[PDB]
Amino acid sequence: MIVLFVDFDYFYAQVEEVLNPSLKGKPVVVCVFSGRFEDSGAVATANYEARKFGVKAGIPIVEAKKILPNAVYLPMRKEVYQQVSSRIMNLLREYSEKIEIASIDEAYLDISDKVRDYREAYNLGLEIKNKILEKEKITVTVGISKNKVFAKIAADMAKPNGIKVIDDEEVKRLIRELDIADVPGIGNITAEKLKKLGINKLVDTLSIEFDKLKGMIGEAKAKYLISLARDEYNEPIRTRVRKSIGRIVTMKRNSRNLEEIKPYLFRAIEESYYKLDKRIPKAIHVVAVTEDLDIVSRGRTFPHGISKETAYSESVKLLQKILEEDERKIRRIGVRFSKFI
DNA sequence: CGGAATCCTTCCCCC
DNA sequence: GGGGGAAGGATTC
Ligand SMILES: Nc1nc2c(ncn2[C@H]2C[C@H](O)[C@@H](COP(=O)(O)OP(=O)(O)OP(=O)(O)O)O2)c(=O)[nH]1
Ligand SMILES: [Ca+2]
Ligand SMILES: [Ca+2]
Ligand SMILES: [Ca+2]
Ligand SMILES: [Ca+2]
Image (cartoon, rainbow, N blue to C red; front, side):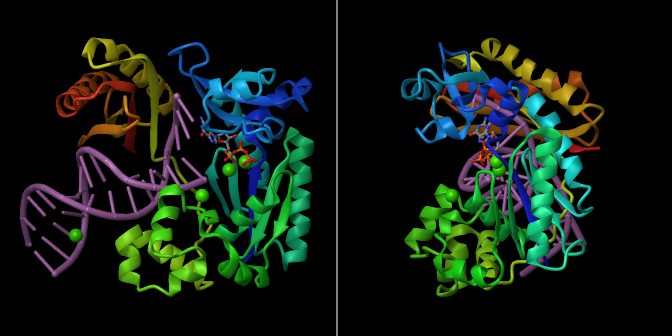
């Protein structure tokens, strides 16, 4: 079982560099401007030049600006990045039919059959890196190991512009040594629940009774961490399909008035339907971000597909359910469509 | 800020 | 008891 994982370097910012190569070597910050005030919003991502001074995804644009007032600041152009991404995914398909497209810039390949060992896999990685650099001018990091999770960890270790193999020797070392928060699927909230159980590396998950562990982090994540620590995680590379299309926008002011919020809600529906492109959903959810950054939602599944008129009509009802049930002001409002025919 | 998958809890109808 | 599904949250990348 040889898995090869491809993670494109600093993706959105690198694409902006490709479309304007004079950006190269400058600090580049790709931003999402919320329209609430001058430079309100956040960093989607940044190239390494900006990153090494602390400008990274998630910080406010305002804070980025005071660290690096002279950086290049660009609005996020997701549609472009998506088209570049799928071209790169298409080239990867030429190296295996077993491909899992995990996000806009991550893919796993099953190269068990195209390759005999880690030496040949490491060479196939170099072929792949070079191919993408030649055809689209994008640097990527490659991780190689015996399963998806360890291929991913490999990439995290080698980035940027890297390639790394975690064989079987190193896999066993990492179970004892890798900080458990660096395990994919362990975010901040789970990392902290695991600390309380005194689980600081993967190996610790075996020293603890299962029912306790699933008591804390849930059954799925429990079985997940256990198989990994046991060196028997072996999930298949699986072709993934879109299950839901949606869109959420930020309001210029926090509000509670139905008629203040509606045009934002309707805009979200309009873009959501364009994105849907001949897909017909049976389910709609109205999603609200309240003033305290909390996320509330109300939804409805239909026996049939939802027409645009029905989306418009139903969304107002669900938004009304939200305002009836939750006393707080709304900051962001949007919709999500799913259960496609 | 933003898009989306998977998972968890609760509640429900009912064999 | 338990299957099957929906709803509203929680959590991750
Ligand atoms: N709007 C938004 N987009 C994000 C955020 N984080 C990541 N993205 C987008 C932009 C990234 O370029 C892309 C890929 O995610 P990554 O975690 O791999 O970061 P990135 O590629 O920028 O750099 P990396 O090489 O992994 O260090 O997804 C975020 O907090 N907000
Ligand atoms: Ca990346
Ligand atoms: Ca990534
Ligand atoms: Ca983490
Ligand atoms: Ca049950």
